[PDB]
Image (cartoon, rainbow, N blue to C red):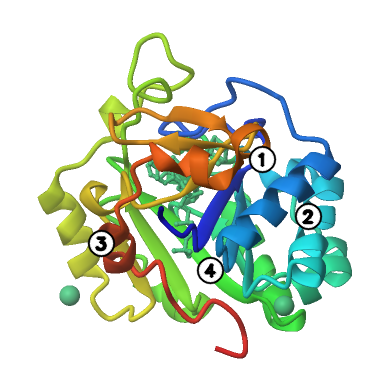
């Protein structure tokens, strides 16, 4: 079966923000108790996991859990790469002082350098850019690789962000085409409806061309993003995106990694093509 080399653990669906396009919505509030999460991460390490990305939901709503799992993954499991993806609003310098030795990469999601755009998207109330520059400084102080995540959508796809990227200098800048997932952001009935925010393949290509001088840019059109991730939900079930859905396997805590992965689609050619294997720690 497939080797789960790089895994996203969406350990909670709770979030403090209202992004209109969110594709991983607040449909539950279950979080595994730490002994269960540690068991799951151990099974993944044994299956060949080298990199773990803590996601959600907003991970910094759970600093006690997140700190425990980061320290366990780096100190006990000896993973090559421990990363977090965050909206940045609840990141405190004290967390980076306490756990920063165990954090390889911190990714901050910021879709625009124009505050009126961040407000229209639902990601903040006007302080996202100032917070992003402060987190960038903290990553330099505590020796953490600084990563920026941008969702390219109808509200920001015409924006020129070169001047801010030249000041921030993230080692890695993910540019995601906004993606529709059935049961998350596709319906009148879901917690979000992203259909008004979608862009064409040509609009996404023009965004990337506008930023051709940024060597850190990692573009992810829908064809590369949809099925190229190994996604563990808040019950440590793999989510299968074959349908354009997020259909859960059995928990790795019930059937093990191999049985859970067996009937999950993971497009390894797409994963390699988007740059899923990279220099993901400081010694790289
Ligand atoms: N159909 C999909 C595809 C991706 N994602 C999520 O989108 C996020 C993308 O964040 P990113 O920073 O790309 O994740 P990493 O795995 O850390 O990226 P990399 O290792 O390439 O730096 C991940 O949490 C991933 O699980 C999702 O929820 N549904
Ligand atoms: C769901 S968030 C979870 C982590 C954290 N709450 C955050 O926003 O960074 C994970 C990543 O997916 C991005 N994202 C969310 N919805 C998306 C969508 N519909 N299409 C593409 N990327 C999306 C986010 O902006 C973020 O970089
Ligand atoms: S993308 Fe926005 S709404 Fe979705 S989990 Fe991250 S901050 Fe929350
Ligand atoms: Mg570090
Ligand atoms: Mg150009």
Q: Which mark is first along the chain, 1 or 3?
A: 1
Q: Which residue is mark 4?
A: 147
Q: Could you say whether the residue bearing mark 3 is in a helix, strand or loop?
A: helix
Residue that numbered label 3 is attached to: 269
Task: Classify residue 269 as left or right of residue 94.
Answer: left
Q: CA distance from mark 2 to mark 3?
A: 30 Å
Q: Mark 2 and 1 residues: CB-CB less than 8 Å, in contact?
A: yes
Looking at the image, tell me whether mark 4 or mark 1 is earlier in sequence order. 1
Picture coordinates of residue 84, whole percent (x, y): 63, 58
Relative placement, left or right, of 269 versus 124 is left
Mark 1 surroundings within 10 Å by alpha-carbon count, few (fewer than 14), some (14 through 19), many (20 or more): many
| CB within 8 Å, label 2 to label 4 | no
Which residue corresponds to the image point at 78% horizontal and 51% vertical from the top-left? 66
The residue closer to the viewer here, 218 or 118, is: 218
Question: What is the distance, in whole Å, between disc 4 and disc 1 at their CAs?
Answer: 20 Å
Mark 2 vs 1, N-terminal side: 1
Q: In the picture, which quadrant includes the C terminus?
A: bottom right
Q: Tag 3 or tag 4, which sits nearer the N-term?
A: 4
Asked if labels 3 and 2 touch by Cβ distance under 8 angstroms, the answer is: no
Q: Which residue is mark 1?
A: 11
Q: Residue at label 2?
A: 69
Q: Of the residues under marks 2 and 3, which one precedes in the sequence? A: 2
Q: How many marks?
A: 4
Return the residue nearer the eye: 100 or 259: 259
Secondary structure under the numbered disc 4 in the rendered image: strand
């Amino acid at each position: 079966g497939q080797v789960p080399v790089s895994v996203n653990y969406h350990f909670s669906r709770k979030c403090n923000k209202e992004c209109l396009f969110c594709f991983h919505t607040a449909t539950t509030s279950h979080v595994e108790k730490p002994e269960n999460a540690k068991r799951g991460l151990t099974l993944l390490k044994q299956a060949g996991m080298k990199k773990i990305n803590f996601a959600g939901g907003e991970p910094f709503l759970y600093p006690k859990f997140l700190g425990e799992m980061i320290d366990f993954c780096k100190e006990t499991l000896q993973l090559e790469s421990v990363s977090i993806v965050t909206n940045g609003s609840l990141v405190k310098e004290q967390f980076l002082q306490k756990h920063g030795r165990n954090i390889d990469i911190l990714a901050v999601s910021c879709d625009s350098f124009n505050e009126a755009t961040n407000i229209k998207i639902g990601r903040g109330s006007g302080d996202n850019v100032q917070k992003l520059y402060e987190i960038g400084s903290w990553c330099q102080k505590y020796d953490i690789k600084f990563k920026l995540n941008t969702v390219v959508n109808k509200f920001n796809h015409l924006e020129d962000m070169n001047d801010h990227l030249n000041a921030l200098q993230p080692f890695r800048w993910k540019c995601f085409q906004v993606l529709i997932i059935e049961g998350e952001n596709d319906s009148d009935k879901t917690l979000r409806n992203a259909h008004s925010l979608t862009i064409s393949d040509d609009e996404f290509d023009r965004f990337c061309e506008r930023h051709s001088s940024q060597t850190c840019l990692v573009p992810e059109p829908n064809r590369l993003m949809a099925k190229s991730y190994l996604i563990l939900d808040e019950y440590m079930r793999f989510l299968n995106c074959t349908g354009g859905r997020k259909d859960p396997s059995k928990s790795i805590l019930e059937v093990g990694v191999q049985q859970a992965l067996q009937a999950v689609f993971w497009d390894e050619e797409a994963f390699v093509e988007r740059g899923g294997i990279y220099d993901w720690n400081k010694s790289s």
